[PDB]
Image (tube, coloured by chain):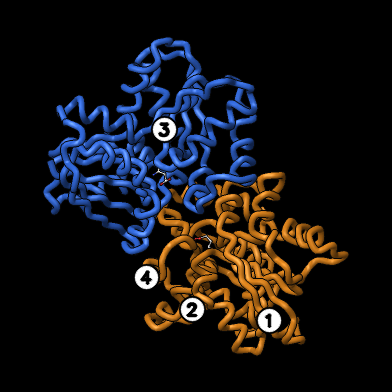
Chain colours: A blue, B orange
């Protein structure tokens, strides 16, 4: 299939990375809305409209499946996009719920959901987890991780202080942490290192990566063999400067 | 007299606050492009197009003067906006140069410009300063101040760590710090405090507030009577959820 990948900006490169490593698709058209990014600090009406405009972008490109790599667009706009599309649209929330069902059999394990403000206020993850019977779920909007990560603050005292800022109030020590944002895989080890240090743990909590979860969902749903497509055609498109977005792709994808 | 104030979002309330305090205008139409904020991390082509589109927003409003409160749009889009406009457009860069001309007679005084990445990259402040003979000029993009301030992080260790991140390499004590971004007034005293601590001063550098500069500039250019309009009509418009933007106004204007 010819696939589209939509994100608000460059964050979706963490999903594209998972897709590319799996070698499942031969043609991928990436579109990042880099003129208007971030979505996570904005309101549901604005985001829903952005999702619908992403469909208009892809319509002339005759894609067969659209991945919404953005957890924020997945949380707020996916249902409206799906109603307006004749092709399947797969977001990054449900695949992570499926991944949890498969990897977390104890329905009382403390799960911590991390995302943008918009993602967390939508309760998309809370509702879906409760529907599957999970009972011990906390959510946390770690808004400032996004701009720190885009400024390449992936280590150091600034990142640690920002983690302290958001994590210190936590009541429950999570056993599972959902990276419900495109950006957060880039600090996954730091988040693991946080909870091991400040809680004297031997093993980190289990982290759920949205890109890895959607690869697995897509392999199951569409019966897609891995390592089948070694030299895919990948095209990059952007609402802001595409050269800027391609330079970021080089960094995020290598 | 009926004016417009244009900003990427809510940062422009720092300028509106200055305008209201002066009580010189009767009718103010504020427009924040809150669907697309920020501008500071984006590219010149995009920002220029955002500026031209702002002119379209104000057409039905019959304004007689447009203030570009945004330092980023001022640095990148002002000239094109002015070329396409039948009304005067006033940005926040030139009024701050005038404030320096008037307050800083020693042309060798060291000046530090703070702003978004786009503002600093444009060199608009350095070029304007050179035009008046100020050649001892340094500049620093302090990108993360914008999202910190929008998250209401105006004090405490997270802000101090962020200031340390940007300021620790500074070796030249500035005599003047230009707050070349709508948001930076909300942490002005913290910036003053930092320099006093870091350079061991008994008195901080002089800070140039963009909003106060443009008010003074406008008072001189149009010979407006301060404290004339005590009960102005103020309208808020936004590309995102205007209720969200008005709520922020309440906080910023208090
Ligand atoms: N792509 C977004 C993060 C950046 C944004 O806020 O737009 C997400 O996955 O939530
Ligand atoms: N209003 C912008 C700050 C926020 C943004 O980057 O849009 C400025 O004055 O530079």
Relative placement, left or right, of B245 versus A246 is: right
Relative placement, left or right, of B75 versus B22 is: left
Q: Where does label 4 land, which residue?
A: B45
Please, which chain is the residue tagged with disc 3 on? A
Viewer-nearest of labels 4 and 2?
Answer: 4
Against B84, is A176 above or below?
A: above
Q: Where is residue B133 drawn, in percent x and y? A: 65, 89
Q: Where does label 1 land, which residue?
A: B136
Viewer-nearest of labels 4 and 1?
Answer: 1
Q: Where does label 2 land, which residue?
A: B89
Ligand 2 neighbours mark 4 (CB distance < 8 Å): no
Q: Disc 1, disc 2: CB below 8 Å?
A: no
* Circle 2 Cα neighbour tier, 10 Å, few/some/many (<14 / 14–19 / ≥20): many
What's the distance in space between the residues labelled 4 and 2, CA to CA?
Answer: 20 Å
Q: Where does label 3 land, which residue?
A: A122
Residue at x 49%, y 74% (from the top left corner): B122
């Amino acid at each position: 299939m010819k696939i589209g990948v939509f994100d608000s900006g460059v964050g979706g490169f963490s999903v594209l990375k998972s897709l590319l490593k799996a070698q499942i698709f031969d043609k991928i058209i990436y579109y990042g809305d880099s003129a208007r990014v971030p979505y996570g600090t904005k309101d549901p009406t604005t985001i829903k409209q952005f999702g619908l405009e992403a469909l208009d972008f892809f319509k002339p490109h005759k894609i067969e499946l659209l991945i919404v790599a953005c957890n924020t667009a997945s949380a707020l706009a996916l249902e409206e996009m799906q109603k307006h599309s004749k092709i399947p649209i797969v977001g990054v929330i449900e695949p992570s719920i499926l991944a949890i069902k498969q990897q977390v059999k104890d329905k009382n394990a403390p799960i911590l959901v991390l995302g943008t403000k918009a993602t967390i206020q939508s309760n998309a993850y809370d509702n879906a987890l409760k529907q599957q019977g999970y009972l011990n779920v906390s959510h946390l909007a770690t808004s400032l991780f996004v701009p720190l990560i885009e400024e390449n603050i992936l280590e150091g005292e600034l990142l640690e202080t920002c983690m302290r800022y958001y994590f210190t109030p936590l009541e429950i020590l999570p056993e599972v942490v959902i990276l419900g944002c495109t950006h957060f895989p880039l600090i996954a080890q730091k988040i693991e290192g946080y909870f091991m240090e400040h809680f004297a743990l031997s093993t980190p909590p289990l982290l759920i990566h949205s890109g890895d979860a959607i690869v697995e969902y897509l392999q199951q749903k569409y019966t897609l063999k891995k390592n089948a497509c070694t030299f895919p055609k990948v095209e990059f498109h952007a609402s802001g400067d595409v050269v800027w977005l391609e330079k970021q792709a080089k960094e995020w994808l290598k």
